[PDB]
Image (cartoon, rainbow, N blue to C red; front, side):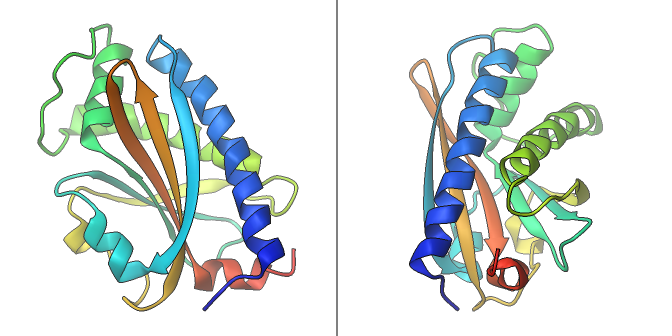
Length: 182
């Protein structure tokens, strides 16, 4: 429904810390300097989901302590750039298609690492171990909460060279609400 002023301040700080960890992690994986800027916004789930590209890499995840799911979404340009470089290539001119089984297998591990960094960012406020529930490439098939429910959307602007892409983490209010006291 809404958040206190203290509450969004806490969330910004948590994810700014995630962002710094993400920058170091991605700088390692893409073997170049990767800048990460974190912004936070509050909007309806329908507004978020309609902003998502077809196709994308959409990972639905939860934690041992969460009653419900959250979303980790990565643009495919970043997905294939990372993937190519991780496999030994230049990261030049990425395709625009759903990933194959092989590519999903490799990049799921990367997402698992990044979710672990997200969990580490949260460690003072709420311990959790992330687990991946589902992976989709079309946001039409992603309806974790009702359209009008408010979500906290964490946007990571990822920039390297002349390129700039995005990773989003979507936290539904119904997931955060029982934790808002902390």
